[PDB]
Image 1 (cartoon, rainbow over the protein chains, first blue to last red):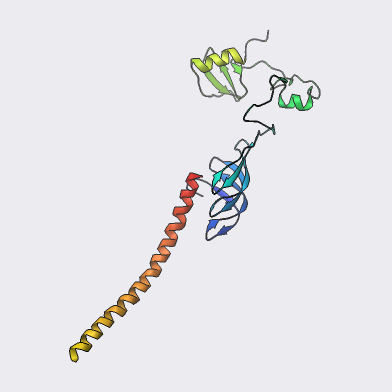
Image 2: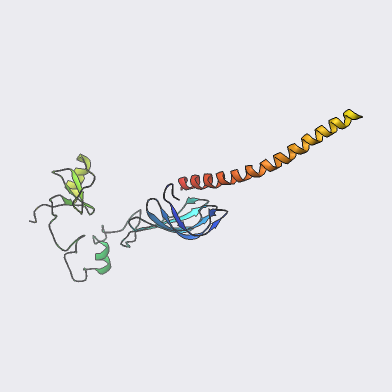
Length: 165
Length: 49
């Protein structure tokens, strides 16, 4: 446990763990899991530091699974993903509700309505300006910086905090 | 006839003592093994996880 930070709540045999259990990993990831021989030997779900869920089934202490779901509960495909795309460009809440229940300007990814404050952009996590090559976090502190390739991607693809025309 | 029992005694004293001491020493090797082993296996398995 201590030497990496791992945590477990369950049963012990010979001093090594054999359990149906909830669990924490020094990612500060949470997990629910079954164990054998002091190893995971279970079908179990991994709850992110960001809450979202990965799933892990264990064969002889190795993983063989596919499922993901976001922390909002959006169900996801790692392949072909049919979402907000050619069949319909609607977000998770906009597909579930349709028109968001009262049509608040959150017919868009984040609102109530405002300009992006600093300048910069929206790319969901962070504000970034192509005139500064800096990303920022929604507390207006900072995020990873980016040269030409990512700068050019942001410049074309997403929404600047231009002045609201 | 004297030297025969001298050798027999010296031999059996040695051999019995050796057996006894090795027997005792074994248990300690057991417990040292146990304590080493449980950590070694836990933390290695942990890493690969």
